[PDB]
Image (cartoon, coloured by chain):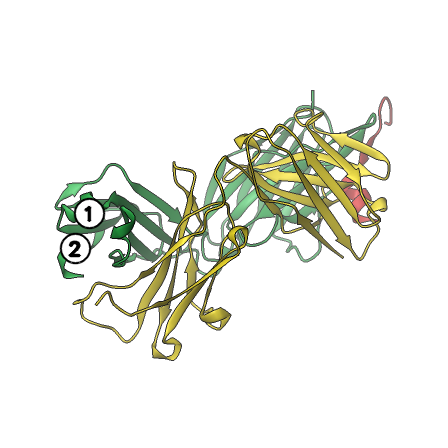
Chain colours: A green, B red, C yellow
Amino acid sequence: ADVVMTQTPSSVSAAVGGTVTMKCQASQSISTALVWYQQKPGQPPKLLIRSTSTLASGVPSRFKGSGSGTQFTLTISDLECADAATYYCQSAALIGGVVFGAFGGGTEVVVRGDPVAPTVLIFPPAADQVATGTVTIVCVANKYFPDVTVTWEVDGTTQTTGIENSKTPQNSADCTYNLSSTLTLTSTQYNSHKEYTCKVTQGTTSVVQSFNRGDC
Amino acid sequence: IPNGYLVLDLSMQEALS
Amino acid sequence: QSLEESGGGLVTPGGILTLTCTASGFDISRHYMTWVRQAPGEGLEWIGSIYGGSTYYASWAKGRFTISKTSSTTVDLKMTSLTTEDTATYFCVRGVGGGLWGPGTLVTVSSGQPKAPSVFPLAPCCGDTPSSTVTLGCLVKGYLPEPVTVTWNSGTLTNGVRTFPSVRQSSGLYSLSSVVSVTSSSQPVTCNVAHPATNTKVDKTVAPSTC
């Protein structure tokens, strides 16, 4: 059977300036033939550490790799918003004519910056949507930390279907998120109700934006 | 101590290529 | 040195596809040229490697994926009996545990024909108090396969652009939105939406309200 790399935890969080650790366990001994990658959207995975503990070029010293055999650890100290990413270990060994090249399952690192409450925008459907048979209403939650929940209300009724959410990566400078939430309805459903409301909740505080179909 | 199948570190081989 | 993958696109379930990794600035023969894939939202997965004349495969890939050297600068990946489980970005890497990666090429295993996006402007409701700085956007809806490229004012407007990750609907089509904060200095503002798979480019000039 191919070597299996078990990576834990699946997600870890710390405040800016803090320290996080993650572990990679190999099902077979691989000496120090193990690397760590950092992955953010926009570019392929970036090599951080090779041969268990050797920093790759340009990688700052706050990243530290340790371990051997079947147990490996990556430690990130003095965390910065730029370190928000998903980290993967990979076996990188040739043993008995077999390449041991399996990846671990990854650890998402969330970096907790300064709290910022969202502002919220709602975008009524452009006039040419309704002819298509479906209407997609877009809500955006701007520049916020920590995470929010979004609900949609139509004439006061909470929607339970037709919602799709997409969150940007944490900002590399200030750790904030941005969120798009869309509500998709048939044209008949859209034309059958008046008020469309996007509600964004952070902790116990909510920010609401609405429009009336007939006004836009 | 080397015994059995030796482990060759391919990440090192790549870094030193 | 650099790597670039090619060959990604839409393929029908049950079909075959060949990807190519093209190297510049080094001799592939001296490295374990390695294929890695990543299904959307999932982890990295080692497929196999080629070092000179020797090939190595992950057990899950043996038989269905084949790696070969096709020139002094290229290795390929031939994949067969494709299903939706094979939808992924495919990357080539110089070395097992190496640092040089291509940008990836996207393989989408789906029965759908290529479908160009519908592009709709995003602007505040008519009759909200206007603002000199306003956030406008474009909704890019109902396309297949990924990717699309979204620019603003033909690349001349870049500061404060937020293009959200695409989301795949249960229908199998994709959608994303892009928004930007603008003053009159960027007006008129136009989103440019290019979709390689349909050879389409849509320019949508976004009025500052729905009026």
Crowd band around label 2 with a 10 angstrom C-alpha radius: few (<14), some (14–19), many (20+)? some
Q: Is A157 above or below relative to A120?
A: above
Of helix, strand and loop, which one carries label 1? helix
Out of C190 and B10, give the one closest to the viewer: C190
Q: Is A162 above or below relative to C3?
A: above
Circle number at residue A213? 2
Of helix, strand and loop, which one carries label 2? helix
Marks 1 & 2, CB-CB < 8 Å contact: yes
> The residue under label 1 is which amino acid type?
Tyr
Circle number at residue A190? 1
Circles 1 and 2 on the same subunit = yes
- The answer, for residue A32, to whether it is visible in the render is no
Q: The N terminus of chain A appears in which quarter of the rendering?
A: top right
Out of A138 and C18, give the one closest to the viewer: C18
Q: Residue furthest bottom?
A: C185
| Dot 1 or dot 2, earlier in sequence | 1
Where is residue A75 drawn, in percent x and y?
A: 59, 44
> The residue under label 2 is which amino acid type?
Arg
Where is residue A207 drawn, in percent x and y?
A: 22, 54
Circle number at residue A133? none
Task: Measure the alpha-carbon separation of dots 1 and 2.
Answer: 8 Å
Q: The C terminus of chain A appears in which quarter of the rendering?
A: bottom left
Out of C199 and A181, give the one closest to the viewer: C199
Where is residue A215 drawn, in percent x and y?
A: 14, 61
User: Disc 2: which chain?
Assistant: A
